[PDB]
Image (cartoon, coloured by chain):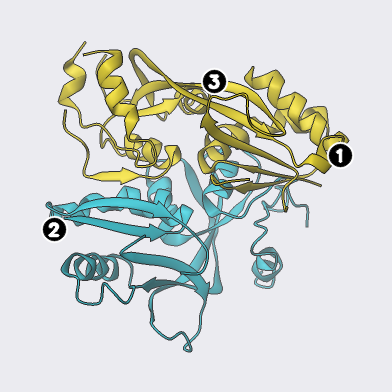
Chain colours: A yellow, B cyan
């Protein structure tokens, strides 16, 4: 048994869609998926979203965070973008301010802590959201949401694998980590 | 005004996000921030899922939990794996007492079980009100009209500093209107 602890949205928007491929590779390893977004005993490996840095401590960068502009599949295909409400993500308020800077507003009246909630709000046609590319990928593929106007944002964040010191030589952990690296480099 | 609510991860995505526009229809001036949590009860109002009890001090029962048997929209039940939810290790046995082979992954949260169903990983048990819109929009389906009264309930907790707060009372009244 491998216990992994990953962000609430990393879990539903990427890991659950992709984990079948890990099980194809290593059928003998059952996985318990926990969720969390705070500071990093129960889990064997964590995935967290942190400002890009070299000074974190048993960690390895999986991938830099690149956000896509997403909207409902009903939206038609420059700054007609401004006609739609922007969905606030309350943990990441700089994102829309940065977007206003990558380019160029009414904010939707509900703000959300997590990407997966913002994604659900886009499915509810409440406005546009910024979602990490790898998280949007399956949802776009299956027709839940669409990428609006090929617009993106480099946020200055990354997804890191963080491993408890005693797990640094655990085989199950190194196998999952290598798998993550393979899919998300 | 801003109202901050703290509800379970799945209550948020599977019910509150699809429904909250009805609240704004009633009260368009009240902005909302939706936080998620599932531990012991910052926020103006909490929704938690607890075993049914009449001994809670200041928790108000919103609705009892009725779980539906859920599968993917392309299901035409023994042939399918059951998706385990680790915080509720008894549920499948207990479902099976009304009338084996679990999936090799996860989860503590309903919203993860729901995604697993979408990923064709097996069958899940999901609260009826949480399944409702996902069923409507064709993400999932209810299998065989099968259900389970789980013994849990959804409780609203109003913190002691919000006891006279209009925005909190309005939101609570709305929840009761929709779910009780």
Is B99 displayed left or right of B21 in the figure?
Answer: right
**Residue B135 circle label:** none
> N-terminal of the two: label 1 or label 3?
1
Tag 1 subunit: A
Q: Is residue B158 above or below residue B36?
A: below
Quarter of the image with the C terminus of chain A in it:
top right
Q: Are marks 2 and 3 on the same chain?
A: no
* Residue A141 coordinates in the image, percent (x, y): 49, 22
Q: In front: mark 2 or mark 3?
A: 3
Q: Is residue A83 above or below residue A149?
A: below
* Residue A153 coordinates in the image, percent (x, y): 39, 18
Is B130 displayed left or right of B99 in the figure?
Answer: left
Q: Is residue A123 above or below residue A104?
A: below
Q: In front: mark 1 or mark 3?
A: 3
Tags 1 and 3 in contact by the CB under 8 Å rule?
A: no
Q: Considering the numbered disc 1 on the image, is that residue within a helix, a strand or a loop?
A: loop
Is B175 displayed left or right of B154 in the figure?
Answer: left
Q: Identify the residue position indicated by label 3 in the image.
A: A64
Q: Identify the residue position indicated by label 2 in the image.
A: B26
Q: Considering the numbered disc 3 on the image, is that residue within a helix, a strand or a loop?
A: strand
Report the front residue among B93 and A82: A82
What crowding class fits label 3: few (fewer than 14 Cα within 10 Å), some (14-19), or many (20 or more)?
Answer: many
Q: CA distance from mark 2 to mark 3?
A: 42 Å
Q: Is residue A143 visible?
A: no
Q: CA distance from mark 2 to mark 1?
A: 53 Å
Tags 2 and 3 in contact by the CB under 8 Å rule?
A: no
Picture quarter containing residue B105? top right
Q: Identify the residue position indicated by label 1 in the image.
A: A28
Q: Are marks 1 and 3 on the same chain?
A: yes
Q: Which residue occupies 79% across, 40% down? A: A165
Q: Is residue A175 visible?
A: yes
């Amino acid at each position: 048994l491998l216990v992994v602890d990953v962000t609430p949205s990393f879990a539903s928007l990427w890991l659950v869609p992709n984990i079948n491929d890990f099980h194809q590779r290593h059928p003998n390893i059952r996985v318990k998926i926990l969720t969390g977004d705070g500071a990093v005993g129960e889990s064997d490996l964590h995935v967290r979203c942190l400002p890009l840095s070299t000074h974190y401590e048993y960690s390895q960068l999986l991938c830099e965070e690149t956000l896509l502009l997403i909207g409902n599949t009903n939206l038609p295909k420059n700054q007609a973008i401004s006609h739609y409400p922007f969905i606030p993500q309350t943990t990441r308020p700089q994102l829309w301010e940065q977007f206003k800077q990558e380019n160029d507003i009414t904010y939707h009246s509900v703000g959300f802590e997590h990407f997966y909630l913002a994604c659900e709000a886009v499915r509810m046609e409440k406005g546009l959201a910024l979602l990490p590319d790898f998280m949007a990928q399956f949802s776009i593929l299956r027709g839940d949401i669409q990428h609006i106007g090929n617009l993106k944002l480099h946020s200055g964040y990354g997804y890191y694998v963080v491993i408890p010191n005693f797990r640094l030589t655990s085989r199950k952990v190194a196998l999952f980590h290598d798998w993550l690296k393979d899919k998300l480099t």
